[PDB]
Length: 56
Length: 49
Ligand SMILES: *[C@@H]1O[C@H](CO)[C@@H](O[C@@H]2O[C@H](CO)[C@@H](O)[C@H](O)[C@H]2NC(C)=O)[C@H](O)[C@H]1NC(C)=O
Ligand SMILES: *[C@@H]1O[C@H](CO)[C@@H](O)[C@H](O)[C@H]1NC(C)=O
Ligand SMILES: *[C@@H]1O[C@H](CO)[C@@H](O)[C@H](O)[C@H]1NC(C)=O
Image 1 (tube, rainbow over the protein chains, first blue to last red):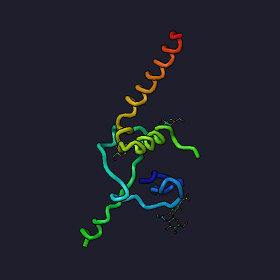
Image 2 (image 1 turned 90 degrees about the horizontal axis):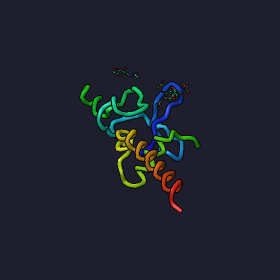
Image 3 (image 1 turned 30 degrees about the vertical axis):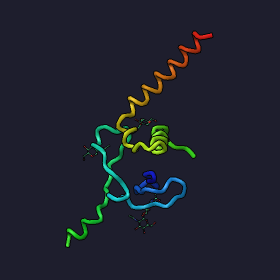
Image 4 (image 1 turned 90 degrees about the vertical axis):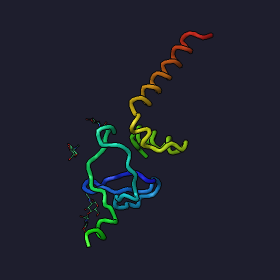
């Protein structure tokens, strides 16, 4: 739920009716297929909250 | 509030209980079906009394 937005330099996801930017993560989001299909997709990092623990 | 039209249609798909990747993956087909369906409105009204 929410929409991807940028302030010009950084990418966030907000709920749609009130500006509240969240850092984009694998639990803010879901995957479907690959980048070649979608008209206007943008290149970015998605943070995975498990990776700091696997970095122990 | 402006929003891109394909991104508004992705909200209309969530509103019927279809996950929005279904629109972004099928976007040209969905656009052609709409454009073709509006063409059938012209041809019906430009013919039927
Ligand atoms: C876009 O939003 C980010 C919010 O993180 C801004 O970057 C932060 O800027 C403050 C100072 O304004 C710094 O203290 C933070 O460390 C920055 N965070 C990061 C991740 O670098 C960014 O300045 C905003 N851009 C514009 C054009 O407004
Ligand atoms: C958006 O419009 C610009 C011209 O205004 C065009 O160059 C660009 O390819 C378009 N991008 C998408 C995602 O449709
Ligand atoms: C996005 O990333 C891929 C892989 O790094 C690259 O091939 C592609 O050209 C990039 N696209 C844009 C719009 O930067």
